[PDB]
Image: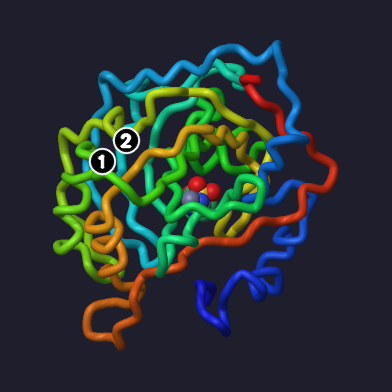
């Protein structure tokens, strides 16, 4: 089954998931000079004050911090979006080295990691229905660079020892995802896909221009996770990113100039 190794990695995914070669695949390179400022883009509204985190799970591909999405508690609205999108989970992709790890790139620059806050359009009733719709999901992407520590990330880092291997979960209540945001909400946006199988073409991508900084020690702790289950051969969970895909017939729009 699929993963990020030599024999089951991104170059292989198209055999089980032909949409891998589709018309609106993610991630992409964001060519800053070619992106178009769109004055018609409304400001992003990130309303996370009532967020209810529940649990953190190592799923064998990344780790997800999951939220109660049975009411409008943590929502994303505005920007390119019509309607209300509920936060269901966030996770990251990261590298084995500080010079790689992000899925989106900016003028071909790779960041050390990339945070994805995954939201679904409430008009579709549940997440499983939403991923079957071209406007079903909105994922807020945030680049990580290595420098100073991100204080709001530390509670995540310190629970990772309890979910080292695939299938492990731990209680993770009262986490505030506002502590993971940069100062600016300036963004690029384009229509795309899930960046792992099943690669469904259901995402409005909103990628923030301003990265957050995390410390060497913080990212080193991500790299101690395992892709494998307990009692299976140890393979470090690193380089769990898909490279940039062809932009095809898409325009990336910018909220700023
Ligand atoms: N990296 S990402 O595009 O933000 C992403 C988000 C969610 C999932 N997967 C997920 O939500 N899977 C369920 C929906 C379809 C099958 C199960 C994969 C990639
Ligand atoms: Zn992701």
Q: Position of residue 19 (x, y in %)?
A: 72, 58
Q: Which mark is residue 138?
A: none
68, 89: nearer the viewer: 89
The label nearer to you, 2 versus 1, is 1
Identify the residue at the far right of this view. 249
**Where 52 falls versus 240 (above or below)?**
above
102, 137: nearer the viewer: 102
Q: Position of residue 18 (x, y in %)?
A: 73, 64
- Mark 2 and mark 1 in contact? Answer it, CB < 8 Å: yes
Relative to 150, is 190 on the left or the right? right
Which structural element holds mark 2?
helix
Which structural element holds mark 1?
loop
Relative to 150, is 242 on the left or the right? right
The residue identified by callout 2 is: 180
Q: Position of residue 22 (x, y in %)?
A: 77, 55
Residue appearing at x 44%, y 23% in the figure: 184
The residue identified by callout 1 is: 150
Relative to 17, is 194 on the left or the right? left
């Amino acid at each position: 089954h699929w993963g990020y190794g030599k024999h089951n990695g991104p170059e292989h995914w198209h055999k089980d998931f032909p949409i891998a070669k589709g018309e609106r695949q993610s991630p992409v390179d964001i060519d800053t000079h070619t992106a178009k400022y769109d004055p018609s883009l409304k400001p992003l509204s990130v309303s996370y004050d009532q967020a209810t985190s529940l649990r953190i799970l190592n799923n064998g591909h990344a780790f997800n911090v999951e939220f109660d999405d049975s009411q409008d508690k943590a929502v994303l609205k505005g920007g390119p979006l019509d309607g209300t999108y509920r936060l269901i989970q966030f996770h990251f992709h990261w590298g084995s080295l500080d010079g790689q790890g992000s899925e989106h790139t900016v003028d071909k620059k790779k960041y050390a990691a990339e945070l994805h806050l995954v939201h679904w359009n409430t008009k579709y009733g549940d997440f499983g229905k939403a991923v079957q719709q071209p406007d079903g999901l909105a994922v807020l992407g945030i680049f990580l660079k290595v420098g100073s520590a991100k204080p709001g990330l530390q509670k995540v880092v310190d629970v990772l020892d309890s979910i080292k291997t695939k299938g492990k979960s731990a209680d993770f209540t009262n986490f505030d995802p506002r502590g993971l945001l940069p100062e600016s909400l300036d963004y690029w946006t384009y229509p795309g896909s899930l960046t792992t199988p099943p690669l469904l073409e259901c995402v409005t991508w909103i990628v923030l221009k301003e990265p957050i900084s995390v410390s060497s020690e913080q990212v080193l702790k991500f790299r101690k996770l395992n892709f494998n289950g307990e009692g299976e051969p140890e393979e470090l969970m690193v380089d769990n990113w898909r490279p940039a895909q062809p932009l095809k017939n898409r325009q990336i729009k910018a909220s700023f100039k």
